[PDB]
Length: 40
Length: 49
Image 1 (cartoon, rainbow over the protein chains, first blue to last red):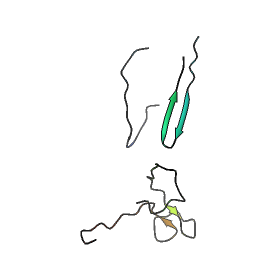
Image 2 (image 1 turned 135 degrees about the vertical axis):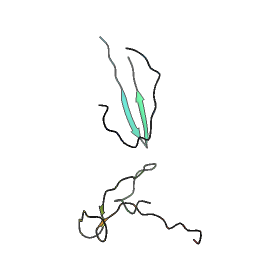
Image 3 (image 1 turned 120 degrees about the vertical axis):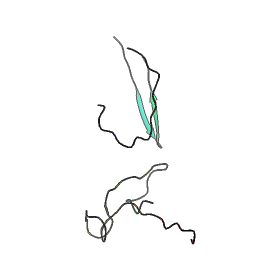
Image 4 (image 1 turned 30 degrees about the vertical axis):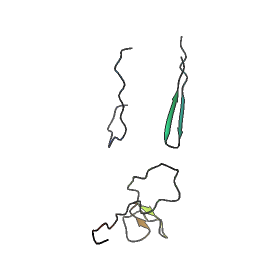
């Protein structure tokens, strides 16, 4: 997946960590805003 | 500034590309001159303006 990228604009790195269940998300791109929901 | 790109965009959205827009009569996919045109145009900002 990590491949030949280009002129990157946005970049955020979360704090590093180390790693029967449900994991349901929601993606919403409205007026240029990306909204994420989740529940476990 | 984007020389021309189809129609109205949605609020707060950008336009960066090298797509040679064929806004002119024919659907040319060249560089410039007629029909096939560069998508971006630069302002003539001079102190004499």
